[PDB]
Amino acid sequence: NKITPNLAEFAFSLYRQLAHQSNSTNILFSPVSIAAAFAMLSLGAKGDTHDEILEGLNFNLTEIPEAQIHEGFQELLRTLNQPDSQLQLTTGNGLFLSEGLKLVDKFLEDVKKLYHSEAFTVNFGDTEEAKKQINDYVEKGTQGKIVDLVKELDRDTVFALVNYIFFKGKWERPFEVKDTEEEDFHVDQVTTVKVPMMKRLGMFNIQHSKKLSSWVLLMKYLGNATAIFFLPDEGKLQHLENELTHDIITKFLENEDRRSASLHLPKLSITGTYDLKSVLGQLGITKVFSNGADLSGVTEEAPLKLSKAVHKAVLTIDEKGTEAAGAMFLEAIPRSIPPEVKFNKPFVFLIIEQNTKAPLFMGRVVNPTQ
Image (cartoon, rainbow, N blue to C red; front, side, top):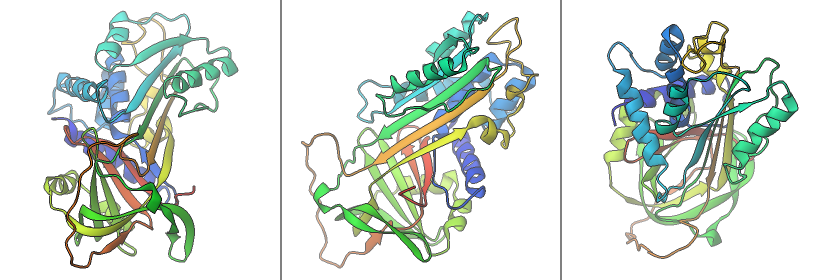
């Protein structure tokens, strides 16, 4: 693409903020999902409000044309929604504005053709009634995978944004349910929990990196997506979180070499729930959540601001290399002795879209049972 580098930096920027607040919490969010959520909102904003958002998404308005930005997100979100995608990425934006409000139709239109988003008007006077609706939107939109998203709503809520994303990929080269068994996972230097561990001896795009002091594993998903897992050596987790760059990751994706290995990877499900206002505030995006928010692109006469913005990400990782079978690869294993690589301790991961090189997900697993 062309806005990929910016997205990559936005992601690490946001990841480090969340990782610095604690080192015992799992982390899971979607760089693409969130950036597009606000790039969209920037269409109904002006001046500092509008400029603050695009720069909080790591865009230098002094060197890049806005049209280029929205131009890119349209194509990116375009390919992510292909009805014939083996990927099966179900993501959506919930725009909820107070009832009885003059909305520029040009806005409601762009939010449609460019950001494939849906805008809804509701009675925010009735809290426990508008909240029950917003959650019924996600649920009926996520095949029920995500429920009771919104916990509570403020009083003077007039503008609320709900961003969600669900994903369960199908490995190009799947694991066998029959080999999955419980193994210890080290949440820390002297503590362990049990977790179902998938395992398979095979040819993997795996290698140990000295610069990162970590094992780097790359696995393909049906639908043109790649998962990159980083298993840091003893005591090098922070080191790893600080050395990661977009170029490092790009180098690893150009390598197609496979080597023998007995891999143990946990079967798990992770979710990330974040308050975009709270989180994006530390990145410099505030004006849009304030009274002085210039949202005249949305409503033309009445005062408007973003009251609440939530992001919810769900990622499931299991054996399946599809709901069904068919093809069937066959790998030639060398006779040499293969290394046993176990992801039985905290590790960081990225899920990259092969076409654009955009990060669909970024996360960290510290405790698989939490």
